[PDB]
Image: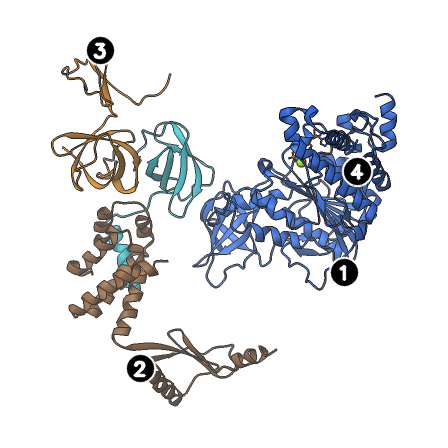
Chain colours: A brown, B cyan, C blue, D orange
Amino acid sequence: EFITVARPYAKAAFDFAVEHQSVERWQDMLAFAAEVTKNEQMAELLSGALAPETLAESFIAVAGEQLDENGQNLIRVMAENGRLNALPDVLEQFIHLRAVSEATAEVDVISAAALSEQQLAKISAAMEKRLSRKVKLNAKIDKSVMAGVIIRAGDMVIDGSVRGRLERLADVL
Amino acid sequence: NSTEISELIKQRIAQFNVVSEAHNEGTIVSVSDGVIRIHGLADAMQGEMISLPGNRYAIALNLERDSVGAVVMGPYADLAEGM
Amino acid sequence: TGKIVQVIGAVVDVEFPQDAVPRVYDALEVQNGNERLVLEVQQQLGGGIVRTIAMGSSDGLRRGLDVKDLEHPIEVPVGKATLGRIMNVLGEPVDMKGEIGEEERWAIHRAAPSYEELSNSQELLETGIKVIDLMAPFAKGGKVGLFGGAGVGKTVNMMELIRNIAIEHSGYSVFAGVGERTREGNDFYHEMTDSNVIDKVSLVYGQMNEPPGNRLRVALTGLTMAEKFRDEGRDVLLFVDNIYRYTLAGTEVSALLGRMPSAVGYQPTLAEEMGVLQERITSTKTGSITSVQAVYVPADDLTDPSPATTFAHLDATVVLSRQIASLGIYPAVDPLDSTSRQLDPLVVGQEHYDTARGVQSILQRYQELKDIIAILGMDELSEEDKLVVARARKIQRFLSQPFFVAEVFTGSPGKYVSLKDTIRGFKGIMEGEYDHLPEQAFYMVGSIEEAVEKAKKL
Amino acid sequence: MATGKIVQVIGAVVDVEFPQDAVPRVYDALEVQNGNERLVLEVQQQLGGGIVRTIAMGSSDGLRRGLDVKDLEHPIEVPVGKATLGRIMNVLGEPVDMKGEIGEEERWAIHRAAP
Ligand SMILES: Nc1ncnc2c1ncn2[C@@H]1O[C@H](COP(=O)(O)OP(=O)(O)OP(=O)(O)O)[C@@H](O)[C@H]1O
Ligand SMILES: [Mg+2]
């Protein structure tokens, strides 16, 4: 999967966007580049063995919403190594590295029923002290947990669902 | 803003005339030792006879995700990339 | 729901929606021209791709075909409805007769019985065959393996064992053809129907014309029928026509499955793939399976991984030698390599045990002398060494025997020899009672009395 | 006009990239300036992307990346007939004796089909 080969390109682009104080734009540019990568006609062209420069300049043709000086270059560097399919993963790591740089975390909360604002306050205020980051909650309450709540941040998970207790108890068999 | 860029992309690719090969048709990507690699042939099937330029065939041995691997039923040396 | 995305020989990759990905060993189904093709799931790759082996010819498959997900494994008919019939790996009827009157179908992938379930037994099972039950006798409920190279006699030996055992035994039997000759499947079926014994026998055939997925899983179809008859509480005979083909069909697919090669290019999983098959062929406190397996030995190399792994699995092992068979001594059993768990004084008793170890000691000493004899000739031997040779050569001839199934080759009529007559004959030869007879007197005679009558006419 | 450029040199194996519509066929002969001599390359494989892979018919030392390559469109061609008698040649059909040029009337390609 392109996750390892996306890493170098993702970091380069972010540091550059920082030194040029233009991070928001880039994220828009990478999103556009990741959508042209999905187009069904372009997906045949990207799979066939065109020469890198004949492919890149054909790729640059289908984007005019790109910062040519900095954004055509990125495309040309990836084309010279055949990497353009990694663009949708380069995007996700750019977003990830940005959130680490902005010291900010997304957090997912799951429960049998919708929470009160006072509970959402205590959850967020706890997690910011757990993480030492800002947090932004989202709530994705569920049909199958019948009581309690789950909290997921990054890949660390805290479970208080009764579902989890019923199985965690049956485990003592 | 996503569906309108998704249809702008469809407009732009049309403007620049970038388009697929026809089904049942493809191009030779590489040539070595009588093994042939073909891109396209989205309707080729395992063990089919693929007609080459001239009056000769290759036999499709592998349907890879991006290509067909085939062996030439004759002299191979006049074949070239992009036929 | 699924789409085909690659076809490489016998292997087909299928993409599914990520909420719906088939389990391992699920059956899939796809329309291939004017017929229906089943695929068996081997591996889950990433991204909803799943990698599968075709139970049939994969030619004419396109990319982009729609694939249907069956929610269950390959399941085959079992029970008495299978008796007297020829079946496909998929459990389809292969005789021209109607549908199989199944009441139940069982998945071919099963777990072996637990260690608590196993049962021991020491009931010696007699055979007609002088060398086998002398040198490597075996029990009811045990496993026997016939090891040999190409053309040495594995099938003729198994056909005498079928004749001798499976007609004085009263219960049901299963014969699994695994990667062997289609002619010999047809020949065997007709002699069963002509003898009206067919109605006790289930036949699964996946012969050597079949593509690798058939040859690999037909063994498991064969066991799953035998496990139904065992769990019903019966005593069952299982015959497997060549176990080596199961491993070889694994080798053929393993590289396409993307597994690094091992050893002499075998699959890395060779010992597990063999072990999980072999452990199911066991007698149990509920009921018994007696098993005979032929084991092809590639390039006559008994140290190749596939023979070598098979030797630990079995209770009696009979090794057939090309060097003996080219003498025209048949059965071409090597008595210095054939062995059994049952050759033990407690179960056989002492007279049998002493006779077998005497024969083994004389024939070993004859191997030690042959390198002297080869250069110098025999005259240089000591007068006791000449007596060892003069006895050993008689013993090698008396191990020969006319088989009833071999009459179409030898012409001379088949013989059945009792265990009492075999130990009496070899014990008499080693005591030297018969040192006045020529070597030809012993060749191809049923019993020691028949040798003395042959000697009168030389 | 030379149309290729050298893109790798790994011992005797030399890789050359050509324009996509010009890629030499297999067994053809290329030539390059190895400083002060022309060096012939024989094509062994057409790789993807206009790259071809070739064996040097001489010493590989002193080749740079980016040297221009002339695509002679035939195979290796050698002089033939009476003019060859009593002469020593190398594989390229160049005289290895000192005895001047060979008065060739034809040159034939070395790779041809059997009767
Ligand atoms: N007891 C015997 N008497 C006479 N001939 C025999 C005997 N055993 C084997 N042979 C001869 O050996 C030949 C091959 O034996 P058989 O067919 O059993 O080998 P096989 O097991 O089929 O070997 P493979 O499976 O590798 O082909 C036959 O011609 C058979 O006549
Ligand atoms: Mg056989």
Q: Residue at x 72, y 36 (%)?
A: C363
CA distance for labels 2 and 3: 91 Å
The residue at 30%/48% (across/down) is A45
Disc 1 secondary structure class: loop
- Marks 1 and 3, how far apart in space? 93 Å
Residue matched to label 3: D86
Q: Are marks 4 and 3 on the same chain?
A: no
C284 relative to B55 in the view: left or right: right
Q: Can you identify the residue that label 4 sits on?
A: C130
Label 4 to label 3, Cα distance in Å? 80 Å
Question: Which residue type does callout 2 highlight?
Answer: Ser
Chain that bears disc 2: A
Task: Please determine if labels 2 and 3 lie on a single subunit.
Answer: no
- Which circle's residue, 1 or 4, is located before the other in the chain? 4
Give the Cα distance between marks 1 and 4. 31 Å
Residue type (three-letter) at the residue carrying disc 3: Gly
Is label 3 in a helix, a strand or a loop? loop
Q: What x and y, as percent, mark residue C86?
A: 71, 43
- Is the C-beta of the residue carrying label 2 under 8 Å from the nearest atom of ligand 1? no
Q: Quadrant of ligand 1?
A: top right
User: Please, what secondary structure does the residue beneath circle 2 have?
Assistant: loop
Output the chain of dot 4.
C
Mark 1 or 2, which is nearer the eye?
1
Q: Is residue C220 visible?
A: yes
Tags 4 and 2 in contact by the CB under 8 Å rule?
no
Q: Is residue B1 visible?
A: no
Label 2 belongs to which residue?
A: A132
Residue at disc 4, CB closer than 8 Å to ligand 1: no
Which quadrant of the figure contains the C terminus of chain C? top right
Residue found at x 68% / y 60%: C113
Q: Amino acid at mark 1?
A: Lys
Up-down relation of residue B23 to residue B4 (above or below):
above
